[PDB]
Image (cartoon, coloured by chain):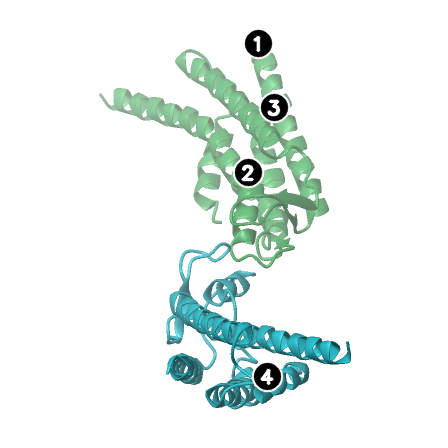
Chain colours: A cyan, B green
């Protein structure tokens, strides 16, 4: 995963952002992207190769892994990172557009319409963070148990399947939840600093 | 398989039987019982152990062998031998009963009621031989093909299964059919010699 281009754009957003916004971006880079690439990806590397079911039925392990893990937590976190970054890019684009328009007018910061877009950016960021949190909760909860009981065809009756690294995965699930909640708190602080 | 007791009783029947009947009993001993024990049993020994199906499905080979071979030819031939022998034992029992009654009357061959029972013995023998022949035909035919196609659950879709020793088994199927037909001819000759 090469996050270079998103990083380069979000550092530009850092130049035009509030101090709390700069904190939020630093959290995104260090506690989400960096952890994901240095720690979590490895943890989940053997998610299917080390997933085992007590059965001689061909195809059962495939369908049972798929049912247990419709989307890997790491993929979900990648999507979450991209969506919570997107409004920042929208605001930065509006910034660059107004700067280029100003340069043109000359040939021939946060107030006004730019402040309205900034605050909308903070709102959409908040809603997307909340949505991904709640989706993670309703899909997986905040804990991975070692045992998964599977009755999906072709599996005969109910089969016992065993997860790879349930405890380490639970640790990182809770870590990422905490980081997301810290991000929400930062957004709320941005909207209370702007309000005040 | 210990045929000693049936043999001992059928040799008694040989003492009280017609010459053609003696031929029939000799055919039974030499061309059915002896072949079954010296040749066929061995041929069919690995009927299930060498039966193979192209599948990874647990249980498929079991159900496919069972469907292909609801009853092994050798078991069928054992039953046939016993049933075609049974009327002979009935006639011999009537003989011994009349002899013991004669000894009693003294204290205090084929005509009459004994001839009626003899001819009924020949009739039931014929009907049982015919019935087993026709049953063998409708169950298996007179040939075993190497390939058996099986769609019985749990087998997925249609599976290719392969028989042990199809050609040797076909040879012995046809041999036993020929021996049974010779027995029928002998019965018919008994009833035409008695008629004449």
Residue at horizontal 50 percent and vertical 72 percent from the top? A116
Residue at horizontal 42 percent and vertical 11 percent from the top? B112
> Residues under labels 1 and 2: Cα distance?
30 Å
> Residues under labels 4 and 3: Cα distance?
103 Å
Return the mark for residue B195: 1
Task: Decide which of A32, A65 is in the foreground and name it.
Answer: A32
Return the mark for residue B184: 3
Mark 1, residues whose alpha carbon is within 10 Å: few (<14), some, or many (≥20)?
Answer: few
Q: Earlier in the sequence, mark 3 or mark 2?
A: 2
Q: Earlier in the sequence, mark 1 or mark 3?
A: 3
> Residues under labels 1 and 3: Cα distance?
16 Å
* Mark closer to the observer (1, 2): 2
Task: Decide which of B1, B142 is in the foreground and name it.
Answer: B142
Tag 2 residue? B77
Expressed as whole percent of the image width and height from the top left, the position of residue B101 reads 30, 22
Q: Secondary structure at mark 4?
A: helix
> Residues under labels 2 and 4: Cα distance?
91 Å
Task: Decide which of A160, A118 is in the foreground and name it.
Answer: A118
Expressed as whole percent of the image width and height from the top left, the position of residue B145 reads 70, 42
Label 2 in the same subunit as label 4? no
Quadrant of res A113: bottom right
Tag 4 residue? A13
| B78, above or below A99, in the image | above
The reply to whether residue B195 is visible in this rendering is: yes
> Residues under labels 3 and 2: Cα distance?
15 Å
Q: Earlier in the sequence, mark 1 or mark 2?
A: 2
| B72, above or below A173, in the image | above
* Mark closer to the observer (3, 2): 2
């Amino acid at each position: 995963g090469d996050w270079s281009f998103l990083g380069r754009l979000l550092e530009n957003a850092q130049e035009h952002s509030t101090v709390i916004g700069k904190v939020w971006l630093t959290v995104l880079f260090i506690f989400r992207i960096l952890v994901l690439g240095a720690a979590a990806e490895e943890v989940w590397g053997d998610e299917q190769s080390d997933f085992t079911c007590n059965t001689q039925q061909p195809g059962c392990e495939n369908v049972c892994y798929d049912r247990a893990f419709p989307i890997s937590h790491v993929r979900f976190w990648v999507l979450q990172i991209i969506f919570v970054s997107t409004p920042t890019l929208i605001y930065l684009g509006h910034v660059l557009h107004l700067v280029r328009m100003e340069e043109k007018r000359k040939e021939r910061r946060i107030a006004g319409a730019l402040l309205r877009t900034y605050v909308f950016n903070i709102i959409f960021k908040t809603l997307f963070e909340v949505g991904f949190i709640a989706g993670q909760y309703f899909l997986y909860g905040f804990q991975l148990k070692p045992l998964y009981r599977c009755d999906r065809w072709p599996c005969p009756n109910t089969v016992d399947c065993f997860i790879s690294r349930p405890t380490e995965k639970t640790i990182f699930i809770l870590f990422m939840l905490a980081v997301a909640c810290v991000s929400l708190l930062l957004n709320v602080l941005e909207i209370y600093h702007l309000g005040w």
